[PDB]
Length: 114
Image (cartoon, rainbow, N blue to C red; front, top):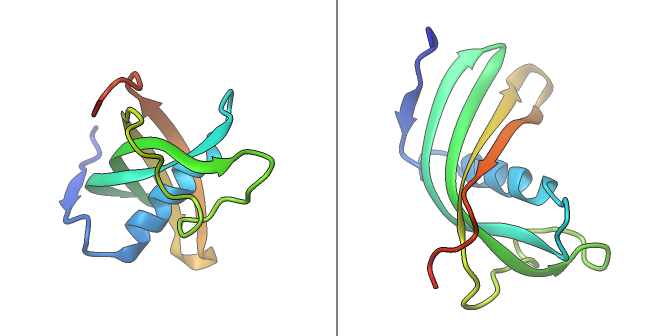
């Protein structure tokens, strides 16, 4: 505000899920395993310098161990019956450099879906 977010269908662009995996996998603090994307719930965008994408997601623990496994969406699938958290990530994309940066990442408690 005065910015406006515009809603997008989460299947419009495969990049939205790539951006989700980028955001989730970048936040490694105090974890033994990477988190991964459970469900991309919604996507909103806003133009400033580049495009800001606000990604609301279910996030939960993957099978990939930090410092043993590199992160990839293909390798780092979900563990079974672990709780999820609701997370909102804001990623900025600069088309003119094909560059992606994480602006913010805010998560609920990791207590759901169990």
